[PDB]
Image (cartoon, coloured by chain):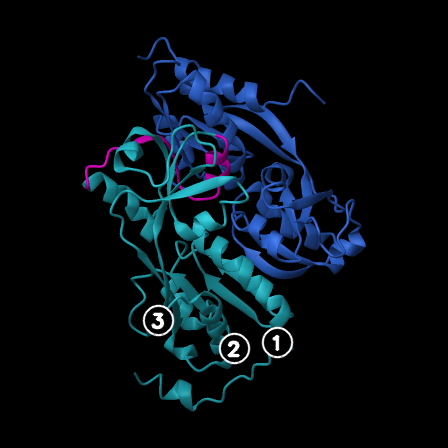
Chain colours: A cyan, B blue
C-alpha cells in the first residue's frame, strides 16, 4: 500500500525506443518462448533495435521475489502464485488439439473419441504448468491412452510425430509453429479439455515505468485476442 | 522376466536421461525403430539436471543416460557414440550471412544465445568471451526449443550443435556454416550403471543405441 505512494512520487526513467539499450528480462514457459519470441523479435528489429531481451522459465527460483526487485520485468502464462502486489491482463486462451503426421495411415480429422483411444500416443509431462494437468484430466475422465512415449517438455514433438505414427495432445498455438515445418495436421480434440488462459503480469512498482509500459503494450498489440 | 529378454513381446518401461538436443536427435529414429522391433515396450525420458541422476541409476529408476556427463565415474560404464561440432545457423535467404562465415561477419551480425546451464553447451559463452570474440547478444534464451522459429523470422544467427542443425535445417528453411571460432567438439556417450551391465533388456537397448547412433566405423 505505502510503497505505491513512494514509487509514484519518484521521477520516472525516460524511455526512447529508438535509443534504449536496456535489457528486459521475461519469464515464460517453453511453449511461450516458442510462441511469443519469433514475432516479438521480428517487431523489435523495426522498433527498438538496440534493446536486449533475455528469458527464463518460471519453474526456476522465486519469480515473485525477482519481480519485486526489478530483476524480472514481465511474466507470461498462468501463474496462480502471483496475486498480491501484481497486476495482470489476459492475452488469450489456449485451446487443445490433436496432432499427427499428414499421411498417418489411419488418423482422421475430426477424430472420434474411440480412435483417440485405439491409437498410440506421445505425452508431455510439463510439470507445474497448465499443460501438466492434461494427463490427470484424461485419466479422471476414464479415457484410456496407450502411452508409447512420455517426454518432459515440448521440443522433440514435431520431429517425433513426423517420423512415427504416434499422436499428441497439444495447445493449438504449438501446432501452428509445427504444422508446416514438420508436415503435420491437426484435428479438433475429441475429449472435453478445458482452455488455459495466458496472462501478462507485472509488479505494481513498475506499473508506471515507461519502458515497462512500452513493452507491455507491444505484447498486447501483437498477442491479445481479448 | 529378468534372466532372458524377448523384444517383440516385452511390456517393460525404459527410462532414459537426455538433454533437450539429445531428445530431439535420439528420439525420432529410436521410436521409428521400436515400432517394428519392440512394439509393446514403453519409453519415458527425463533431463539429467532433474532429480538425482547418480542415485536414480543405482536404484534402476533410470536405465540409461546420454551426454557428456562428467560426474558419472565410479560405478558407471561408458561408451562413445559421437563427437559433434558447433556450427553457425541462419535463415536461408538472410540478406548478408554467408557459409563459410568469417569471424569478422560473425562478430558484426546479431545473435541469439542459448544459456544451456549445467550442460556441455553451457561453456560456449565463456569460451568465446575469453578468446575476445565479441557478440551483440540481442536475445538470450535458456534452452533450444524456440531457435528454429526465431531464426526463420529474424536476421539473427546462432551457435548450435550440428545434430541440432540436422533436425531444424529443412523444417525451418535454414542454412548452416562451419563455425569460425575454435570451439571444442563435445563428446556424447552412452552411460549405464554397473549393476545393470549384464541385464538382458538394458543390453538390448544399448545395442540398439549403438546400431542407430554410433559412428565408430566411418570417419
| Label 1, residues with CA under 10 Å away: few <14, some 14-19, many ≥20 | some
Residue B70 in sight: no
Where disc 3 sits, the SS reads: strand
| Label 3, residues with CA under 10 Å away: few <14, some 14-19, many ≥20 | some
Spatial CA distance of label 3 from label 1 is: 25 Å
Relative to A175, does residue A54 appear above or below in the rendering? Answer: below
Residues drawn in magenta? A141-163
Q: Residue furthest top?
A: B4
Q: Residue at x 47, y 77 (%)?
A: A213
User: Does the residue at mark 2 contact the one at mark 3 (Cβ under 8 Å)?
Assistant: no
Residue B38 point in image, percent of width and height: 40, 18
Compared across the picture, whether B19 is left or right of B179 comes to: left
Check residue A184 for magenta coloring.
Answer: no
Relative to A42, does residue A34 appear above or below in the rendering? Answer: above
Spatial CA distance of label 2 from label 1 is: 9 Å
Disc 2: which chain? A
User: Does the residue at mark 2 contact the one at mark 1 (Cβ under 8 Å)?
Assistant: yes
| Label 2, residues with CA under 10 Å away: few <14, some 14-19, many ≥20 | some
Q: Which circle's residue, 2 or 3, is located before the other in the chain?
A: 3
Disc 3: which chain? A
Residue named by callout 3: A88
Disc 1: which chain? A
Residue named by callout 1: A20
Where disc 2 sits, the SS reads: helix
| Same chain letter for marks 3 and 1 | yes
Residue named by callout 2: A211
Compared across the picture, whether B204 is left or right of B120 comes to: left
Viewer-side label of 3, 1? 3
| Same chain letter for marks 2 and 3 | yes
Spatial CA distance of label 2 from label 3 is: 17 Å
Q: Quadrant of the N terminus of chain B?
A: top left
Amino acid at each position: 500500500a505505502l510503497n505505491t505512494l513512494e514509487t509514484a512520487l519518484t521521477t520516472r526513467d525516460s524511455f526512447d525506443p529508438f535509443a534504449s539499450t536496456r535489457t528486459f528480462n521475461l519469464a515464460m514457459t517453453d511453449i511461450g518462448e516458442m510462441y511469443f519470441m519469433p514475432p516479438l523479435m521480428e517487431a523489435l528489429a523495426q522498433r527498438a533495435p538496440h534493446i536486449q531481451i533475455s528469458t527464463l522459465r518460471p519453474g526456476a527460483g522465486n519469480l515473485k521475489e525477482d519481480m519485486e526487485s526489478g530483476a524480472v520485468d514481465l511474466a507470461l502464462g498462468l501463474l496462480p502464485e502471483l496475486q498480491t502486489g501484481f497486476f495482470q491482463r489476459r492475452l488469450f486462451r489456449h485451446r487443445y488439439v490433436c496432432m499427427f503426421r499428414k499421411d498417418h495411415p489411419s488418423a482422421k480429422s475430426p477424430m472420434s473419441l474411440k480412435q483417440f483411444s485405439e491409437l498410440e500416443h506421445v505425452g508431455v509431462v510439463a510439470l507445474n504448468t497448465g499443460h501438466g494437468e492434461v494427463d490427470g484430466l484424461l485419466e479422471r475422465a476414464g479415457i484410456k491412452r496407450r502411452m508409447r512415449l512420455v517426454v518432459p517438455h515440448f521440443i522433440a514433438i514435431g520431429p517425433i510425430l513426423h517420423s512415427t505414427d504416434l499422436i499428441a495432445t497439444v495447445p493449438q498455438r504449438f501446432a501452428v509453429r509445427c504444422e508446416v515445418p514438420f508436415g503435420l495436421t491437426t484435428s479438433p480434440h475429441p475429449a472435453k479439455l478445458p482452455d488455459i488462459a495466458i496472462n501478462l503480469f507485472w509488479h505494481a512498482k513498475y506499473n508506471r515505468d515507461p519502458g515497462n509500459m512500452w513493452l507491455r503494450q507491444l505484447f498486447v498489440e501483437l498477442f491479445s485476442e481479448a
